Amino acid sequence: YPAKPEAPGEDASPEELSRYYASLRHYLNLVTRQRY
Image (cartoon, rainbow, N blue to C red; front, side, top):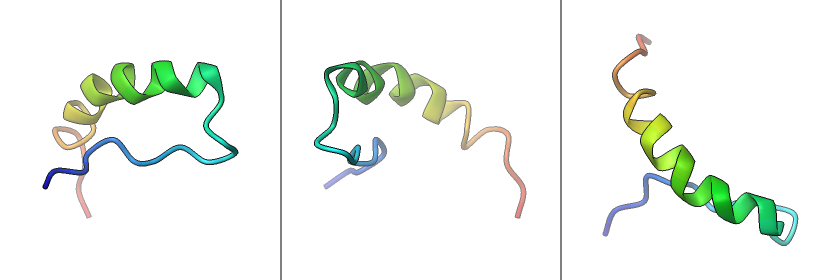
């Protein structure tokens, strides 16, 4: 049961659907550039 891409708010606009995929890659780059 993975859950990397968080659920968008505000009824999730049709533009936010594109975020549920492009952000999945940017998410890999988020866990590889953080500290505390």
